[PDB]
Image: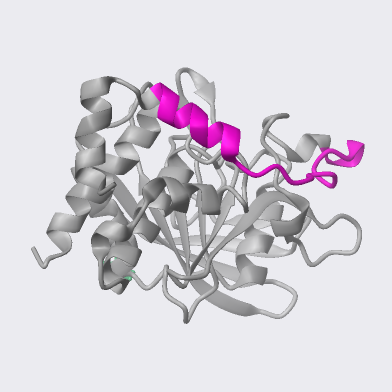
Amino acid sequence: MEMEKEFEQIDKSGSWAAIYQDIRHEASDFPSRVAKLPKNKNRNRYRDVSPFDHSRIKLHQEDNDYINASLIKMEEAQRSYILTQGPLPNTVGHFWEMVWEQKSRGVVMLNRVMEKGSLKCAQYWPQKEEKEMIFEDTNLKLTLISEDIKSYYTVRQLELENLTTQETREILHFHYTTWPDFGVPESPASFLNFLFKVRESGSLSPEHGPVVVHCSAGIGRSGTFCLADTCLLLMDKRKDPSSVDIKKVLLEMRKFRMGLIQTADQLRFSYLAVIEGAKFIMGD
Ligand SMILES: CC[C@H](O)[C@@H]1N(C(=O)OC)[C@H]2CC[C@]1(O)CC2
C-alpha cells in the first residue's frame, strides 16, 4: 500500500502495536559473540543491545578492537551510517578513535546528557574553547572551536588532532536537544528541519566517511533518524515514489543492527516524518 493512506488505515484501526510486533518477529537474528566476551562488559551500556559480529565497527588496535557500534550500509539509497551507543566513561577515547579511523565528518547526538534524572551518556566533548580534552588511552586531542545554539538544536565546530601524527580535522557536532523525556514529538517539523541541516553540511555525503549517530542505546531515536533519511532519498531516486515501503526499509536496516525503532510510537512518528518530509522536498 502507499504510505499516507496505510497510515490513516492503521490510525483508524488502532493497530500500531500489531504492526510493530510483526516487524519484531520478522527481524534478523545474527550472532554478537564479540560483544558478549567478559573482557567487554564495561564497554556495553545495556546488556540486551549489542552489535552483530558481521557489521560491527572494529577499532584499529591489536589489544582490544571492540566498540558498541554498527555499520548500516544501504545499497540502493547509496548511504551509510554508523549507529552507536552514547559513550561511557571508559569508552570516550574509543569513540573519538572510531570517528578518526572511519573518516567521519559529522556526529549526530539525539539525547541530552541527563534525562529522567539519570545519566544517558558521558560529557564527551568540551564545553569551553579554552578547556580542551585529551584522551590519553587513544592519543587524541579535542577542542571546541565554535558553538551555535538554536531553539531545537545546537551545532558545534570541533577540532580533532591525532597526537601521534599531528594531523588535524574539523568535525561537526549536530545536537538535537528537544526530544521529550517520554514519548515522541507531537510534530515532526523540528526533527525534519534538523535532518536537513545535517544534510546541508556535507556530513552525509560520499566524499566523507559515514556519519556517526547516537542516542543512549543507539537503536531508538537513532533508528528514526536514518530510517527517515533513507526513505526520503529513495523517494527522490525512484520513478514511482509511492513504491517506497517503510516497513521493508526498516527490516533491511535491522540486518545490520538489532532493535532499530524501540516502540510503536517511534514507528508511527517515522511514518509521520517521511510523509511530511516528502511534501516539502517538492517539489514543495
Ligand atoms: C550553518 C553553518 C554550519 O552550521 C557551520 N558552522 C556552525 O557552527 O554552524 C552553527 C561553522 C561555520 C559555518 C559552517 O557551515 C561551518 C562551521
Locate residue 281: give its quadrant.
Answer: bottom left
Q: Nearer the viewer, residue 246 or 122?
A: 246
Locate residue 269: give its quadrant.
Answer: top left
Residue 53 falls left or right of residue 118? right
Q: Quadrant of ligand 1?
A: bottom left
- Residue 150 placed where, x, y %? 23, 48
- Residue 193 placed where, x, y %? 22, 53
- Residue beneath the point at 78% across and 44% down: 32
Residue 46 falls left or right of residue 247? right
- Residue 2 placed where, x, y %? 25, 49
Quadrant containing the C terminus is bottom left
Magenta stretch contains residue 79: no
- Residue beneath the point at 60% across and 42% down: 85
Residue 243 falls left or right of residue 211? left
Residue 185 falls left or right of residue 166? left
Magenta stretch contains residue 35: yes
- Residue beneath the point at 85% across and 44% down: 33
Q: Is residue 178 above or below residue 238?
A: above
Q: Nearer the viewer, residue 168 or 54?
A: 54
Q: Which residues are magenta?
A: 17-40
Q: Is residue 217 above or below residue 137?
A: above
- Residue beneath the point at 55% across and 42% down: 218
